[PDB]
Picture 1 (cartoon, rainbow over the protein chains, first blue to last red):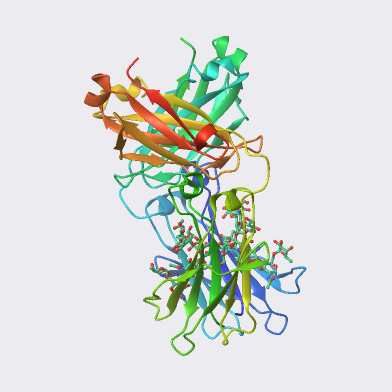
Picture 2: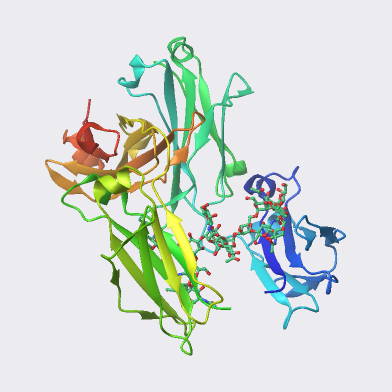
Length: 209
Length: 209
Ligand SMILES: *[C@@H]1O[C@H](CO[C@@H]2O[C@@H](C)[C@@H](O)[C@@H](O)[C@@H]2O)[C@@H](O[C@@H]2O[C@H](CO)[C@@H](O[C@@H]3O[C@H](CO[C@H]4O[C@H](CO)[C@@H](O)[C@H](O)[C@@H]4O[C@@H]4O[C@H](CO)[C@@H](O[C@@H]5O[C@H](CO)[C@H](O)[C@H](O)[C@H]5O)[C@H](O)[C@H]4NC(C)=O)[C@@H](O)[C@H](O[C@H]4O[C@H](CO)[C@@H](O)[C@H](O)[C@@H]4O[C@@H]4O[C@H](CO)[C@@H](O)[C@H](O)[C@H]4NC(C)=O)[C@@H]3O)[C@H](O)[C@H]2NC(C)=O)[C@H](O)[C@H]1NC(C)=O
Ligand SMILES: *[C@@H]1O[C@H](CO[C@@H]2O[C@@H](C)[C@@H](O)[C@@H](O)[C@@H]2O)[C@@H](O[C@@H]2O[C@H](CO)[C@@H](O[C@@H]3O[C@H](CO[C@H]4O[C@H](CO)[C@@H](O)[C@H](O)[C@@H]4O[C@@H]4O[C@H](CO)[C@@H](O)[C@H](O)[C@H]4NC(C)=O)[C@@H](O)[C@H](O[C@H]4O[C@H](CO)[C@@H](O)[C@H](O)[C@@H]4O[C@@H]4O[C@H](CO)[C@@H](O)[C@H](O)[C@H]4NC(C)=O)[C@@H]3O)[C@H](O)[C@H]2NC(C)=O)[C@H](O)[C@H]1NC(C)=O
C-alpha cells in the first residue's frame, strides 16, 4: 500500500447559492519520502481541465506527505450531474489512482417541509422540542437551519438523511427551546435548501396557537 | 497483504429480550483461494470460552472469501459490559489479529418517548406521517417498532440515533399511513425497547385528537 486518495464533494449549500464557491478536493495521503512527487490530472465528464489549485506537499507527523488539489466547480455543472475525476500519479504506484465524484443520479424531487409542535406530554419539562420534518427529497444533499426573529437558533440537531421506501429521502431537525419561549408565542422557523426547491429555498414557521 | 477482521455487537433487541439470542460476530474478509483456512479463538473478559460457530463461507465477486464466526452471549454479560475478544489466526498473515468489543460505557439513561400527529399542512396528501420522537437515552442501542390493534404496522422508517448536546441520544421514527386510517380514528403506537426502561419496553399511543 503506497499512497491513498480521497475525493470530497462540495458542501450542499455551496452548490445552491451563486454567492458561494463550490469545490471538489482531491487529497493524497501516505506519500513516501523515497517517492514524494505527486501529479494531479483533473477531468470533467472525461475531458481534461487545467484550472485546479494544487498545494505543495506537507509532511505529517507520521513521516508521510499529504498533498491536496482543489478544483473550483460551476454551480450549474454540479447540478447538471457532471462527473469530476481526479487522477493521481506517483512513482510508488503500479498504476495512477483515479477517483470520480458527482451528485447522485436520479430525477430531483422537491422536499415537503412540515413543522410539528411539542407533544403535550413534553410540556411538563423545562425545555421543549420543536420538530421540522423534511420528506420526499432527492438527491439527499440538503441543508436545514432554524431561526426566530431574524436570528439563528443554535440549539438544534438534524438527523442524517434516511432512505424512504419510495426511493426518496427524509430527515428530521429538532430545535430545543426553553418552555417559556414557546409559551410566550415566539415564532420559530425551519429553513431548507435543496436543488428541487424554487429558488433552492423554503421556510416554514411554527408558533403556539 | 492478507485477510482483515471486523467484530460486530449484538442487535439491541436481542440483548433486551430473554426469548431472543444475542450474538457477537467476527467477520473475516480478503481470504484468498491460495490461503484458505481460518481459525478463531474467543474470549470473555480474558477467560477463554468455547461456545462458537463458523458459518459456511461465501465466494465474493472479487474472487476472495468471506468467513464468519458467531458467538452466543448471555444477555446480562453483554449488559454488564463484559469484553468480547475475537483472535483470528491465518498462517498467511504476519501475526494473529485480535479485535475487542463491548457495550458503550456510562450510566444508562431512560428514553423519553413522544408521539406527534401529522402536520395540518400534510392533511391534503393521500398518505400522512405519524412521528415518534425518542430522546434523552444512553447508550445509543435501541429498537423502535409500530403497531395498531396489537398487529405490526410495517410501513415505517427510523433515523439512526443522533448525539444530542447533553451527551444523550435522540432519534425519530416515521410511520406512513393512508389518511383514511388516520381520519377514521385508529390507534397507532410506537414501541420502544431500551435497557434503561422498566421491563426494557414502553409504548405510546397516537390517534386523531
Ligand atoms: C499519516 O497521517 C495522515 C494525516 O493525518 C494527520 O497526521 C497524523 C500523524 C495524525 O496526527 C492524524 O490524526 C492527523 O489527521 C493520515 O491521513 C489520513 O488517512 C486516512 C486513511 O488512512 C483518511 O481517512 C479517510 O477520511 C475520510 C474523511 O476525511 C475527512 O474527515 C476527517 C475527520 O473526520 C479529516 O481529518 C480529514 O481531513 C477529512 O476532512 C474533510 O476534508 C475535506 C477536504 O479538505 C473537506 O471538504 C472541503 O472542505 C472545505 C471547507 O472545510 C470546503 O467546504 C470544500 O468545498 C470541501 O470539499 C471536508 O470539509 C472535511 N470534513 C471534515 C468532517 O473535516 C473518510 O471519508 C474516509 O472514509 C472512506 O474510506 C474508508 C477506506 O479508506 C472507508 O472505510 C470508509 O467507509 C469511507 O469510504 C467511503 O464511503 C462513501 C459512502 O458512504 C463513498 O462515497 C466513498 O466511495 C468511500 N471511499 C472509499 C471506499 O475509499 C477515510 O476514513 C484521513 O482523512 C487522512 N487524514 C487527513 C488529515 O488527510 C494517514 O493515514 C497516516 N498514515 C499512516 C500510515 O499512519
Ligand atoms: C472483496 O469483497 C468483499 C465483500 O464485498 C462487498 O460486498 C459484496 C456483496 C459486494 O456488494 C461488493 O461490492 C462489496 O465490496 C470486501 O469485504 C469488505 O471489506 C471492507 C473493508 O475493506 C469491509 O468494510 C468494513 O465494514 C464495517 C461495517 O460492515 C458492516 O456493514 C456493511 C454495510 O455498510 C456490510 O456490508 C457488512 O457486512 C457489515 O454488516 C454487519 O454485519 C454483522 C454480521 O453479519 C451484522 O450483525 C450487522 O447487523 C451488519 N451491519 C450492517 C449495518 O449491515 C465497518 O465497521 C468498517 O469500518 C471501519 O474500518 C474502516 C477501515 O476498513 C475505517 O475506514 C472505518 O472508519 C471504520 O473504522 C473503525 O471505526 C470505529 C468506530 O468509529 C473505531 O472504533 C475504530 O477505531 C475503527 N476500526 C478500524 C478497524 O479501523 C469497514 O468499512 C466490508 O464490511 C466488507 N464487506 C463484507 C460484505 O463483508 C473486500 O474489501 C473485497 N476485497 C477487495 C480486495 O476488493
